[PDB]
Picture 1: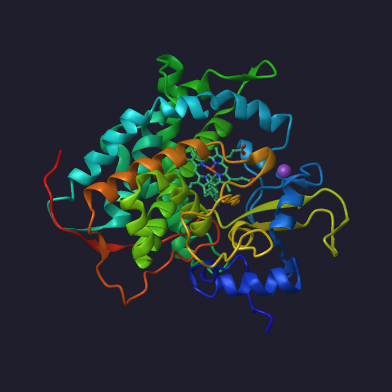
Picture 2 (picture 1 turned 120 degrees about the vertical axis):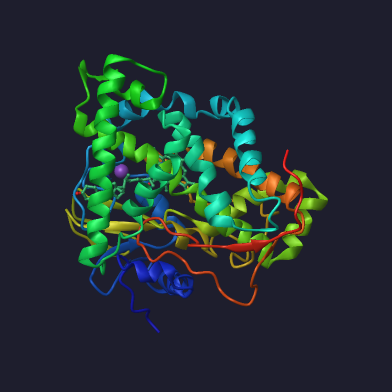
Length: 395
Ligand code: HEM
Ligand SMILES: CC(C)CCC[C@H](C)[C@@H]1CC[C@H]2[C@@H]3CCC4=CC(=O)CC[C@@]4(C)[C@@H]3CC[C@]21C
Ligand code: NA
C-alpha cells in the first residue's frame, strides 16, 4: 500500500489523496524516500528535528528541488541570513503589523464593496488573491493600478513549478521573471536617486558588513518578499473559507461568537498549509530518524504532513476552529520561521471577519463538485471558488 509519489510532481499536491500518502509516510517511513529517491521529513517530529539543526540541514543549497541557490535570504544560513532578515523585518513585528490594521481593514471592505451587490463572485479571484497583493504591494511601493500586473507575474512564477512542466509553460515562467526583472531594476535606479519609505528603497540603501547589496540580490530579495506576500495567504483565505462552508457548523460557530475568530484562523492555517514544502541540504552524512542521509542531498520538509500528524493533533482530519493548542507548522519553525507570519495572521483575521459579517449567508455555488487545486510542487491552493450570497450595499 506504499504510495507511488514524486514529491516534485505538481499533480501530487493537487490530488486529494495526498494526505493519505502522508499518513502512510508517518506510520511506515517517517523520513520518506519517493519513487525518485528524494528524501522527505513527513512527521512533525522529523520536521522539527531538522529545523532545529540548521548547521546540518542547510538552506544554502536552495529551498527548492532541481534548483540552485539564489541571492535571497531564504537561500542563506546565518550569519548571512540574519543580517538580511534584520534589514527588512522592522515593519513585520507583531506591534508594527497592528499599526497597519486600519489600512488593511479598508482594503478588505473596498474589495467586498466590489462584489457585494452582485450576489456572486470568485472567492479566489475577487477576494482571496487581491487582499495580500495590495497589502504587500503597498509595502513594496507598487502602484495600486499595477497590482494585477504584479499578481500575474507572481502567478506565472509559482504556478508551473513541477517536474513535468511543459517547455512552453516554463517559457511563461522565465518570461514573467524577465518582465519582473526589468521593472524592478528600473525601480532599483529610481530608489537610488530618489529614496522612499517602501521596502525596495530600504533594500537599496542597506549595507551588510560595510557594503551595499548587489542588484542581483536586491532583485531577488524583493521577489522573495513579493511571492511570500502574494502567493501564500491567498490560499489559506480561500481554502480555509471553503472548510468553513463545507462544515457549516464551524461557520455558524463563528457568527454566534466572533471571539472564536483567532482560533479559526489558526485552524485555517493548519489545514491549508499553502507552502507545501521547503528543502534542506545536508552538510554531512548523518543518521536521521533511522534513515541514512548523504551529504549534499536535499530533503523536503512536508509541512502539510506535519500539520495532520496524529502524534501531535487530536483528530487531525476534523476541521475544528476550537482546536487549542494548534501548534501547526504552516509558517515553518526555527531560523527561517516566516517573517510575514504576523502580517498574514492579520490579513486573515480582518478579511475573514468581514466575509463572515458582510456575506453572512455565503455558500459555494456547487457543493457537489470539488474545487480544483493548483498542480504545483511549492505553493498550492484552490484555483477558483465560485460562491453565492445575498446582495447587500457597499460601505
Ligand atoms: C499564510 C501565509 C503564509 C505562509 C503559509 C507562509 C509560510 C512560510 C514558510 C513555510 C516559510 C519558510 C519557513 C521555514 O522553512 O522554516 C516562510 C518564510 C518566509 N515568509 Fe512566509 N508565509 C506566509 C505569509 C507570508 C507573508 C505575508 C510574507 C510577507 C512578505 C512572508 C514572507 C516570508 C519571508 C520573507 C520568508 C523567508 C524568511 C526567512 O528566511 O527568514 N510570508 N513563509
Ligand atoms: C513562499 C516564499 C516564502 C518563498 C519564495 C521563494 C522565491 C521567491 C521563488 C521560489 C521558486 C523560484 C523560481 C525558481 C525557478 C526560476 C529559475 C530562473 O532562471 C530565475 C527565476 C526563477 C524563476 C524563480 C525565482 C523566484 C522563486 C519563485
Ligand atoms: Na537551515
